[PDB]
């Protein structure tokens, strides 16, 4: 361990790479600086709740390969990672507060076989040599692999993974993982799940013919083509901006469509990675706004499947949907056999 | 009062909504965090000169309806608001340092009828029940309403208002208010005033045929059409970029026209809401710059009216114009019956 | 000296201009505020390693004329400036930690003729009266002028200079300087040098017919036209995104071409001004990434000249090129008389 050594690696290798060497370091203002040719240059600003120098080290020792999005790990109940740091780029902080064989200040253990780790769900990366076997010996754990594991039934994970804070479907690298989980020394069967698409509002990319049609076509043209009469897409997806309180607008693709033609404000008042997000929206054009707007990025085809697979005979009820391996509650309101609204409740 | 309760509301409702409940809270680094599933998530970064936890509470209890822009309130001499917080999004801080019936740390009173409030100009919102009557009983105050008040002559305010930091002309909600003011227990007659348009440089929207022509047409074509020869629009509005010191460029629409074709730097060295703004501009293309460039966003039609309504017989003089209810001083330079320049002086 | 006076100047003149007057000032949170109509407004946030009030003063007293880019001054070995502050906008801090006749807290001297300055390479600005003569009397120094100096052989500097953080080729102002340097009281002959173009990725402007062709034409079309077969532009300039480790992509123009069609992430892990830059790149489309990607912004014509002026008979060797007056090392890899790669090594 050495602050100056960590700094040397960041300067010379872009991250911690176990290289020998030292550079001069100063710490002020929750910030780490290094001296370059007689002047101080900022290397790291600490936005975590850890000590500046500890956060610096964990950031430097972050996983720089494609890794599961934090929301996936959280949903599977991961407490800690084996011999790596999953950096949470949404929070600009470590996904997990403790480590195993990374950093002396945050380590609870050097190896995941230590008894302190037993009650924790440890994340194992099958791409790293030996970690598949560690998962077999672990009481509680989650495992990812690129291929088959002998004697374990896989769960096909999302297409996308996070690489240095960039969520992408890898072409030059593999981002689709098989998932395995153990609880109390017993291999679990992971449930059937939809997956969120983890897209952003600005450069929203469609991933189906339906989504291409939605973005290109007008509202009534689209609803007609896919026979979505009575499912209240006008409200739920397209959004209603007629009243002071903004109605619906619960699918990300719907936001992307409007943002294209008419910008608006999104306040991310809980800035973290989560399967579904709450935003305080204010529509700049109309002045329609709402304090808590639940937004989820499902493939529109998946959302259509879900809403078409519900009974529409009651006024209001909770609808449970497994998304990203967690149970998301939706509220379904109907009237005379038609949907009034269908939105996630967090 | 309760920090944890305020936090609960922000997490669950997006703002303070008087709901019961508590969440775990940590305060570090002038920042408020809450614990979500074993990890700390940032709720609020304090950029005010108040204590972090006080600023947090005032922000949470901000007015989330369309409200007057801070510049309007400042110009009318408002010192404090009755039973609400006008959040200043330009400064990312409370518009007023004291409160009435909001927060125990900043309250000077629970109700505006208390004698401490007498010398202060209190802001009353007629949309809130009872506040019209409080204004009648108040010695010093400013009132807004959507409609008529019995026995009071109104002043028609700006078309636009601020909703959650977004200045807009409301369609789904009403943003145009009637204004009333009292001084020493006497109802004032508010002066005839122009209003600034409160637009931004990037997505500048024209609001007249003249403004559409200005943006579309070339300089000489426009000046010809509206017979603006001798009023020196070339300098004042379009701007002169021939010399090291940038000449003119005092209307926002003029900046918007050039930014469209040729980007430049604007240093907002006094970041606050004000009827007219001073910027340190540097033109990227030419290298023409000026330390103090006074810029005001008047409707071009209004600006044309003002400059055409002046005597042009003297070399230099001060011209007073009521804008946003305050007296803005302009310097008018003329030569042989022609304008040389006409710009606001702050 | 006076904090309140410095603040008065910033408020009234946009920078320090030696005007008399005072405004109320508060210092909290490494931030300087001033009181305007009963509310605090932020004037300056300190991002330097100096005391907040010292950094404020140096920033206020920054040079607001076109000045050499910091990388140029660093390369020429400048330690200090005579009677001015070169503000480093890349680091948001003073380029030099000490001053001469600027600020009482940072001054080592009032005038550069003081004996403390003898071992330091002082930067002299010939546009300022008397400083040419000070350079003649100085033991160690660097001088810039707009025109000829009697009895000194000039070095023609870059076309571009920095004006208030904006690098530009001046039209309304002169940005091309003659350079002179003295070491141990002896005038030096500055070496023949290429210059970097100091452009940015987003609004990349071509400055030759070759560069226009590169941006417009496809890869194979361009390589054919300029007979660049065997120089491995496919790898070096255009970049290879086929493997998990990103190959090549060492010219800024190459990044600009791809960013146009396909965005990517650049982590500037040493945020300073330097002749060549190291970035941690992650390609959003492919997932191809690399921790240390050396990038230099040479005019493509200059880069073509350099690579065509090398012997290609050995497997690997270091190639030294004078750029921005400093020796930049390139690694040249060849195979059977063809280039494999040619990239800067820092
Ligand atoms: C309008 O209230 C009458 C009964 N009702 C409610 C809802 N809806 C459906 C709907 C469809 N489109 C637009 C608006 N509402 C109806 C018909 C809600 O979705 C709702 C959500 C959260 C709290 C309460 C309610 C609620 O009471
Ligand atoms: C050039 O000085 C000769 C007299 N004069 C001055 C002005 N103008 C008008 C003008 C019109 N277009 C471009 C430039 N100036 C003239 C003709 C100013 O506007 C001015 C502003 C602030 C301080 C002083 C002056 C000032 O003295
Ligand atoms: C692939 O290794 C076999 C020998 N070699 C190496 C290089 N190249 C050229 C090349 C051209 N295009 C793409 C990739 N490489 C070859 C042929 C490097 O550039 C290099 C850079 C830094 C450290 C080591 C090496 C290195 O060893």
Image (spheres, coloured by chain):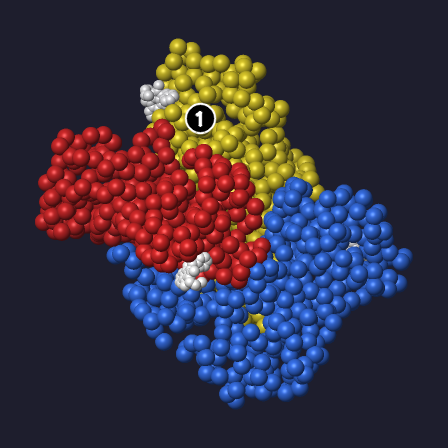
Chain colours: A yellow, B red, C blue
Q: Quadrant of the C terminus of chain A?
A: top left
Q: In this view of the protein, can residue B226 be seen by the observer?
A: yes
Badge 1 crowding class, 10 Å Cα cut-off, few under 14, some 14 to 19, many 20 or more, is some
* Residue pictured at 11% horizontal, 48% vertical: B184
Q: Is mark 1 within 8 Å of ligand 1?
A: no
* Residue pictured at 12% horizontal, 38% vertical: B136
* Residue pictured at 53% horizontal, 78% vertical: C129
Q: Is residue A133 above or below residue A24?
A: above
Q: In this view of the protein, can residue A49 be seen by the observer?
A: no
- Say what secondary structure mark 1 lies in: loop
Q: Is residue C330 above or below residue A80?
A: below
Write down which quadrant ligand 3 falls in.
bottom right
Residue B176 placed where, x, y %? 30, 34
Is B211 on the left-hand or right-hand side of C20?
right
* Residue pictured at 56% horizontal, 84% vertical: C134
Residue A88 placed where, x, y %? 51, 48
Is B229 on the left-hand or right-hand side of A113?
left
Reading the image, the residue beneath label 1 is A239
Res. B6 image quadrant? top left
User: Which chain is indicated by disc 1?
Assistant: A
Q: Is residue C24 above or below residue A154?
A: below
Residue C94 placed where, x, y %? 50, 69
Q: Quadrant of the N terminus of chain A?
A: bottom right
Residue A344 placed where, x, y %? 43, 28
Q: Residue furthest front?
A: B336
Residues A48 and B214: in front is B214
């Amino acid at each position: 361990m050495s602050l100056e050594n960590v700094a040397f690696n960041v300067v010379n290798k872009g991250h911690f790479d176990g290289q020998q060497g030292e550079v001069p370091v100063s710490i002020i203002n929750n910030t780490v600086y290094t001296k370059v040719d007689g002047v101080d240059v900022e290397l790291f600003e600490n936005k975590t709740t850890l000590p500046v120098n500890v956060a610096f080290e964990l950031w430097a020792k972050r996983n720089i390969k494609p890794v599961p999005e934090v929301k996936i790990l959280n949903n599977l109940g991961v407490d800690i990672a084996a011999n790596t740091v999953i950096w949470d780029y949404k929070r600009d902080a470590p996904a997990h507060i403790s480590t195993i064989g990374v950093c002396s200040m945050t380590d609870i253990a050097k190896k995941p076989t230590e008894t302190i780790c037993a009650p924790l769900t440890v994340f194992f990366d099958g791409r790293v040599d030996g970690q598949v076997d560690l998962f077999r010996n672990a009481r509680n754990g989650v495992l990812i692999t690129e291929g088959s594991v002998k004697g374990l039934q896989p769960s096909v994970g999302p297409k996308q993974a996070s690489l240095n804070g960039v969520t992408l479907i890898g072409e030059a690298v593999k981002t689709q993982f098989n998932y395995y989980k153990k609880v109390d020394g017993v291999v679990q069967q992971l449930p059937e799940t939809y997956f969120t698409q983890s897209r952003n509002l600005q450069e929203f990319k469609p991933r189906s013919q339906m989504e291409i049609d939605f973005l290109e076509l007008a509202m009534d043209e689209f609803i007609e083509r896919y026979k979505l009469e009575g499912y209240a897409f006008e409200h739920i997806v397209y959004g209603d901006f007629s009243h002071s309180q903004l109605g619906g607008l619960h699918l990300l693709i719907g936001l992307a469509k409007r943002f294209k033609e008419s910008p608006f404000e999104l306040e991310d008042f809980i800035p973290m990675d989560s399967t579904v997000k709450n935003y305080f929206i204010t529509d700049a054009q109309t002045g329609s706004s709402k304090c808590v707007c639940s937004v989820i990025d499902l493939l529109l085809d998946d959302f259509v499947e879900i809403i078409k697979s519900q009974d529409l005979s009651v006024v209001s009820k909770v609808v449970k949907v497994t998304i990203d391996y967690t149970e998301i509650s939706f509220m379904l309101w109907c009237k005379d056999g038609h949907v009034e609204t269908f939105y996630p409740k967090l």
